[PDB]
Amino acid sequence: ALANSVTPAVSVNNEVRTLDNLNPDVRLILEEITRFLNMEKLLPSYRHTITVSCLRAIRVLQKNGHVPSDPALFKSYAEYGHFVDIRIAALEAVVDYTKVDRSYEELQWLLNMIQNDPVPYVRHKILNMLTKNPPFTKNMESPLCNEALVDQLWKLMNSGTSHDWRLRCGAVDLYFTLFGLSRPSCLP
Amino acid sequence: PHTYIKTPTYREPVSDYQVLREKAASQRRDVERALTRFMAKTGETQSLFKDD
Image (cartoon, rainbow over all chains, first blue to last red; front, top):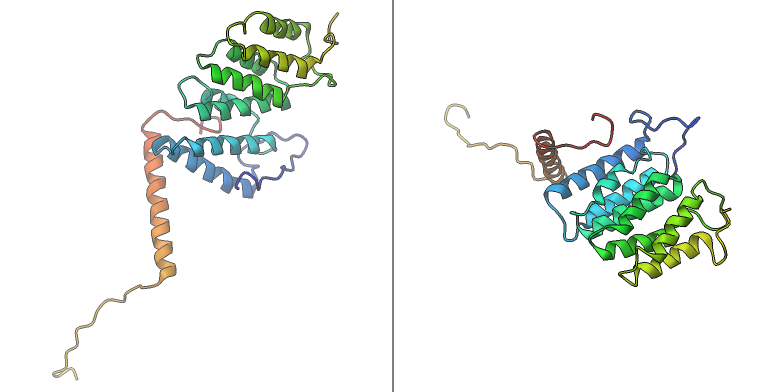
């Protein structure tokens, strides 16, 4: 409910979002989610439901112009040793970031995590979230439509996902969502 | 009356639900803020802002 109340901020001349030019409304929300996340670090919930809700709310505040658009927090919560709900919430935030900020290195981070993660459910979920919220569609001109990305995703369909039967269908779905049924257009 | 009259007297009791809710709420908020600042200062810490 605190995350639902966040309206987009009135940035002037692309002003850098710092602590002093914060909204007086959003400072209370940010204090509350900081208190909740830190108290979850000491007294945890049943399935880290407050971690998932606070990561989702920090992504809501980053989607508007309130918190700086930095994926390092979600990249630290998406490591292997965390609970799987925290991991998929953080990876959902990283997928949303690499859709909005057109990040090349975050997409390479996600594709590397698809290739070598210990939990195969997390790999399937990353391919699923990158299909649902794709970094670009076939209609879009994006900076991320190289021949290098077409070769990486074709290598991920062909080899690489050969051991799961669910990662390979997810890679086929991702290639269909990104490049369509015909020849990838952004290619010689 | 002062020559021989004595009545005990007590302190003013605060039986008000509003101020009791306010006292318990503010004391709980202050002790949890003090606890979390003490535990963040004497351990590894993160920060939403640069060097915060």
